[PDB]
Length: 279
Length: 274
Ligand SMILES: C[S@@](=O)c1ccc(-c2nc(-c3ccc(F)cc3)c(-c3ccncc3)[nH]2)cc1
Ligand SMILES: C[S@](=O)c1ccc(-c2nc(-c3ccc(F)cc3)c(-c3ccncc3)[nH]2)cc1
Image (cartoon, rainbow over all chains, first blue to last red; front, side, top):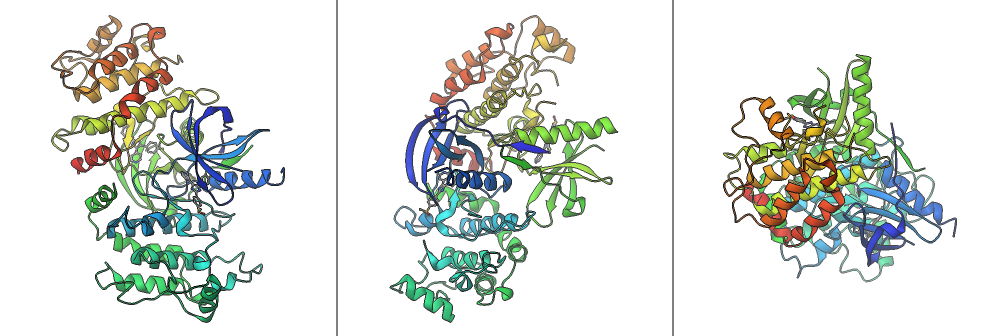
């Protein structure tokens, strides 16, 4: 059973407005003149033409509840762009570090975010053939209208989410199914702390040296208080994921099985209250 | 062509397969994917014609992918079991939200209008497909509600109160008729044709140009946007199919209404249901 991705005439997008730069390109918001929905458009050589068409192919094949939904492709002599559902609430990074805009980010939502990132990345790994993210960062973990996760920019510059064996990449590191879990371990640490990993450190070059030595962000009372739900299980999960040996790192499936009970300790209502709190 | 193949799910990967209800084609059960770690819904009949009917529904769902259409996760196609796997909708259907008044004494206006906006967005996407895909069985019972009380339409392109009189015998003007009745029902929270004992009495009444009662009792004068909504309902359910609006027009009418509601009003209409 095959589903073709719709082709969207550029002239069908109205109210086109700049939002930001994406992974590679500009991200604009617009509205579909016929579908009557708000959309996001990622737009930018006939070499770079197959580049945009590759992301579109990946998003289309990687379709799932925690992966950014692609609506169609603009493929015209005058314009090339990917059209997706519009994500109103930015990225994880901005929820985590825009502390004036967001003074509180409730534990139910934080853990829900973590659970959804794992459910997302895991789906990529369970595809046939396995799809690898390799650039999982807080900046590309997008938040929908009700602050649910949509992962983007996978399978296509902050080194803090990079495993040390990828610093000088080989064929083995670029095919490594244990890169994403290191990134996830740094994100988990960052989410539970609301702190910038290696904040104290001056050079990103310096970070690379200590990270390659063995140093990870600090796991202590100051960064991760004792009042953190399931702290022991969490700290175990982080340290297990950012393990210097790729072979000593858990799969996303193993983490999920560990996270499933954690999330069940939060009353359904608390997730909804956490969201209302951000508004 | 950018093609995507619908995943094949092995029946052994669908754990805790516990019954939910029935559905148009067959039985609806809830389950969990072993590897993906998510709650899912499975649709299976409880024979070659039935097999071709099931795969056609799954082809429709996979081709009709949009924000307000039930998202299909994969096909479970084995000799032991044949089922359609989709996301799990934990909040029932629009029918239950409207008529389970004990469970839901208050269903706030922002949410009712959002629900109507999203049914129209879903049906409008179908009509905009190439070729246009007509629903022809739009009813409150197959308008599903997800985790955030957003609409997901199901049982499209495959009870008599949502059927236009001319259909009692494939026009693009059928769905708007159904939509007009659903709108009446969402705004009133009343069963269309309350007094009627036999579905034939409804069918007779409708064919004679009669419709669910628009009065102060069915539609209180304090309903937001009452004049506009009545006008959309009355045009939608016109005896003349040609006097009925397109879903585009129907959406152009609804857009100024939805702009009057801030996102928080939707969040607090949902928390009130909890
Ligand atoms: C009341 S009757 O008219 C009726 C019709 C359809 C359904 C009904 N059909 C489905 C359903 C499931 C999978 C499919 F592929 C197609 C439809 C669901 C469903 C989907 C996701 N999560 C929970 C339930 N509910 C239930 C009752
Ligand atoms: C600057 S950081 O690297 C960064 C990376 C990606 C994005 C970013 N990329 C996208 C985006 C859009 C379309 C695609 F096809 C792929 C990604 C979005 C997006 C999607 C839907 N609604 C709003 C925004 N945001 C924003 C910031």
